[PDB]
Length: 56
Image (cartoon, rainbow, N blue to C red; front, top):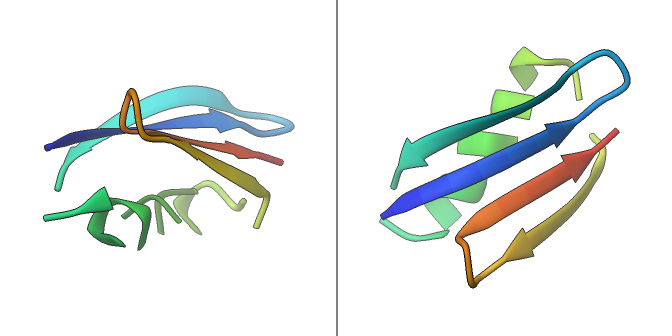
């Protein structure tokens, strides 16, 4: 399915998507994607929209 990641970092704020297996696969893409953008951060997931959010 299509999963979404919302970035809210100090210098960067954005949105990206990925086609993933399970919400595991997508979380362990995003948790490298937020790697590429130099963010640990605080994480939440929203099952209704299949959307992750990370806040720096």
